[PDB]
Image (cartoon, rainbow over all chains, first blue to last red; front, side, top):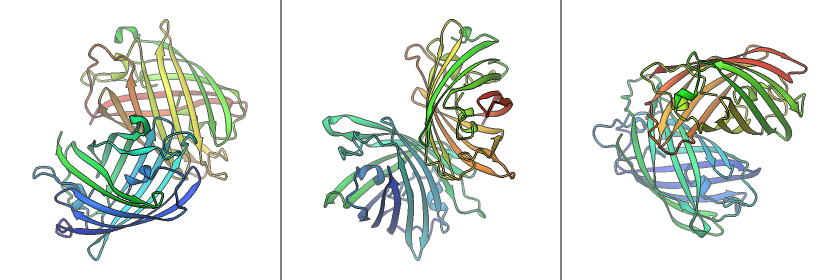
Length: 219
Length: 219
C-alpha cells in the first residue's frame, strides 16, 4: 500500500464551494516528495473569480500524504493506498466565520486525485477575510489522536492580518482510510509541525502557487 | 475548587439565538447531582415561540459540570470554580445545517448561571428540523482530548427522524476554564457516555423538560 506512494508524486485537485453564498471552482496541478514532507501546488481560480474573499481560507484544503514520519511512527496516510482516504474539517474563526470541508484523496495511474467541497458561512462583511486583508497562516502543530479505524487532528491556527495582528482559527479534522480489508498499523498520539508558505500569486489572487513543509514528531 | 460544587446544585440559563433567519430567547430553571451525573432542566421558549424548528437542535445547548468522574479521571469542569468555564461548539448536519454556539458557565451564590448564544444557518427549507419531524437524540459518547489549558470534545451524534431514520451530526466542542491562576490537574484522553431524554413538553414545544445522565470512562 506504501510501495504505491513513490519518492516523487504528481497530484491534481478540484475544489468547489460557496463562501457567504459566493460560488467558485478552483483546479490545481503540483508535485512533491512524500517521504521528505514537502510539496508545491499551482492553483487557478477558474470560476467565480476574483473571489470577494481571502484565498487563505481555501489554501489549507489543497494533502497529509506528504508528511515526513520518522521510523517509529506508522504513517496512516501512505498505508491507505491504493484506495486513499477522506478528511472532514471544521474551521471556526474567532470573528464568527465557520468553514466545513469534505475531501476525497484517491490514486489513479500514479497520480494523487484531490476533490474538496468547501462551505464557509457567517464571515462578517467588514472582517479581514471578506475584506482580503490577510498575510497567510503562521507555522503551527496538529495533534493527531487515533479514533476507531481513523485519526482526529486538532490545530490552533493563526491567520496573520493587516497591522500585524492575528485572526485565530480552530481546525478540527477527522481522517478516515478507504481501506476496509487490511491490517493498517495504527499510530499512537503524535504531532505534525506544518508550514504553509505562499510562493507566488497573480491577477487579484486567481493564480496561486503554494509550498507546504510538514514533519511528524513523537508526543 | 470542587468544595463549591455540592451534592445538589440548582441552575438557571438564558439562550438567545437565530436559526435560519428566525430569532428566539429561552430561559431555564433546573437542578441535579454532579457527582451522580444526573440533572433535570425545565425550559420555556419566552420569545419567538412557537419556533419554526425542532427544539432538539437547542436541547444539547442547555452542562458538563454534571458528569460522574471515576476517582482516577480528574474533573476539569468542577476545578474551574469559582470562575467556571465557557464552551464553543459547531454542529455540522449532513443535510447542510450549521449551528455555532458560545456558552458561559459561572457561579453566583451557589447557583450555576448558563448564558448561550446560538446561530444556525443553511437548514434545508424542507429538511426534518425545519419541518419539526425529529424524535430526540440517541445515547452517544463524547471523546474528550486535552489542549493548552482547555479540552476538545468530539461526538458523532444521531438525531432521530419520523419514519425511524437519523440525521447524523458531528459535534465539535472546545471547553476553556476561566481560572487562569493555580494548578487545575489536567486529564488525559477520555470519554463521556451521555444520554439526553425529553421527559415532558407542551404548548407547541414552548415548555420542555429534559434529564441528562452523563458518566466518564477510561479510553
